[PDB]
Image (cartoon, rainbow, N blue to C red; front, top):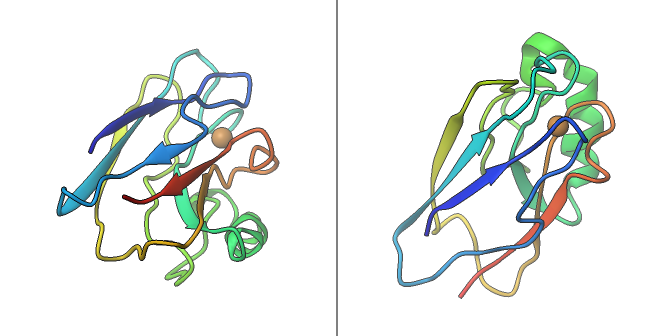
Length: 126
Ligand SMILES: [Cu+2]
């Protein structure tokens, strides 16, 4: 596995490169959030996808807007999204690891309006 990742008010993250073990049936991510800069001024998503899909889930996800969770509905290009948290929250995602092959490249990110540039990392498997 579990990671404990957290973003600031800088538009950053920490763990801009994850590694999930194969000797582990599921994976869980926990997002937290640090200063008082609300979920309309700095919210952070932790969405996962492959570095060939991101443009979908960033773009289509900024289309959706706030309420939709800056990440559209269904998106079968996401294997894991937490939700848009903000200052003082925490949330979590407990996904399968079936859902990921090995020898694929997966990037993670925050679909809020422009933080998918400084907030990206990688998820390789194992
Ligand atoms: Cu963000």
